[PDB]
Length: 208
Length: 208
Ligand SMILES: O=S(=O)(Nc1ccc(O)c(-c2c(O)ccc3ccccc23)c1)c1cccs1
Ligand SMILES: O=S(=O)(Nc1ccc(O)c(-c2c(O)ccc3ccccc23)c1)c1cccs1
Image (cartoon, rainbow over all chains, first blue to last red; front, side, top):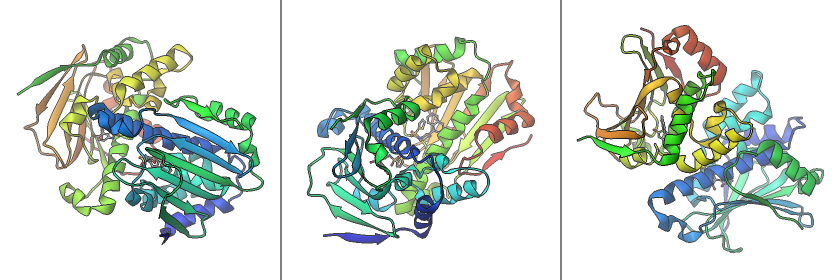
């Protein structure tokens, strides 16, 4: 029912560098997650151009940001193309192995963590703020799966029995106890307006 | 043998704005083309992760920049995933219609042409420098096609009889007579080092 996998070695080293490096501008995680949502949305929209039944599983293309101060989670929901099980296992549909190689080389020579997105591995910046990240996802061609990792070199995959999502991806960020400012309306808005002003999809910040 | 198509109205307006707006920093076209090559390369690499026969049509993933001062062309070749005929007709595998809408809205309120890539329509910046652009392309699932446009509201598509490319895309830029500085070794290198320093594929500048 639950499958446990080892991260590839270079992805574990990336996750460790992100968890351990002293670096204060942690707010960039949101930009990287939202830009991934936008790319997934760009994809389903492209497919729908020539096949509108691709949107049978939901016509609206949007991003939702949902803070929950009780659970201490920040959730980013998009109704993009989503991921098959095979995508999730392969580093969440990314060429992460070679993206890590380039990113760690760039660091050694000048670069800082904020440039992570340029190497195609922005997702792992969630670990600047989250002790555990849970990706729920549903692709037209597959069933609904949950991926999960508290880092430490392994991640799990299970078919998800939670709330059906139609199509898309939900990234649930279980936040480190000192990172709860990202659950504050004030701070989220500041970040989105600063870093995501030219995303082509409505972004709705849920209030509690 | 030759099919002629009308640009969608908003793509023609984008092309016209790019051709007519007074704007001096035209050098950005190269960054936008090379970043498209990188994305096509990211794609074939991803597919190959789980199916290595995807690289039967060529194992090397690279970008070539080829100036020809005689023909007055600058060519950008990549061995990325390439495009099917259907992709080429649909605005070269992009959601160009809605990307134009966002880009022209951003312009009206602050933005400048250099941000074109953020709206997913970087390709059309080739018209800052080229009087005519010819895209040759080959995708594993289709035959080799050539797309062509001197703007003016129409583009053509034909199956290509030129030199077989295996897999990838060649963008041939027939340069405006006052834009020949982009055929100079000096200037190309300046531009690549400035704007494309973190592309994850070798870029080889051909000498004449
Ligand atoms: O080209 S993509 O595979 N687009 C894509 C497709 C489906 C998806 O569910 C996502 C996606 C999201 O929509 C949301 C979060 C993601 C986190 C890691 C990887 C992909 C995420 C992204 C991509 C992956 C990583 C950055 S862009
Ligand atoms: O997601 S993509 O469809 N990637 C992709 C796939 C195959 C390709 O041949 C290209 C591509 C190139 O490799 C080179 C030039 C292009 C110009 C316009 C559109 C796509 C170009 C780009 C994309 C299209 C436009 C910007 S990124």
